[PDB]
Length: 206
Image 1 (spheres, helix red, strand yellow):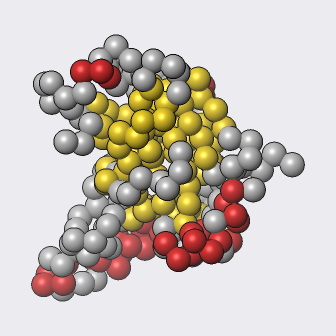
Image 2 (cartoon, rainbow, N blue to C red):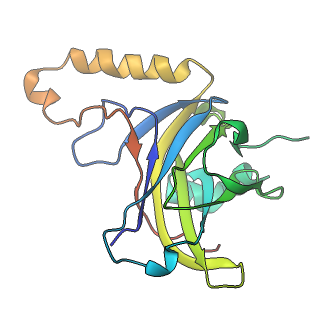
């Protein structure tokens, strides 16, 4: 099935319709926890038992046409769009920030062990209010240390604000929903206290 689950520890907006993708507001530069979980039932991928996997994280534009045309705005002194807060992280092995892709980081982890990566996002949605996508692609190696066999990809939709802006936008969403009729409130999903990433197409290259 789906061998892993990734949980971004930030609440979703309460102003999204029932069956639409979640939207999560983040503050620029704030460390956010992403829990890396084994989602396998008994028996799946025993080759993973006792080995590590590699996850590659990207922050890209959520709209596909905007990503197709403006991807280089996020890719690239010392000005990164995505970074790993290594001192706060747990179970994060050999973390690396790609010096040529300022919106990409990677690390190894053991799905049998507690694993929480903390990330900071430094691009702001209004410097282009466009949504971004946090995407994770996860790989195994086959005995030569090359983590190149794709296992799983998932992603979530975010907007990033200058700090406190995410709290402000979440408050505006709450106060907008409070004004709506009962019959219209029913058409929206509640805010969830974490953001569970959902399966997506693999990134077209490793």
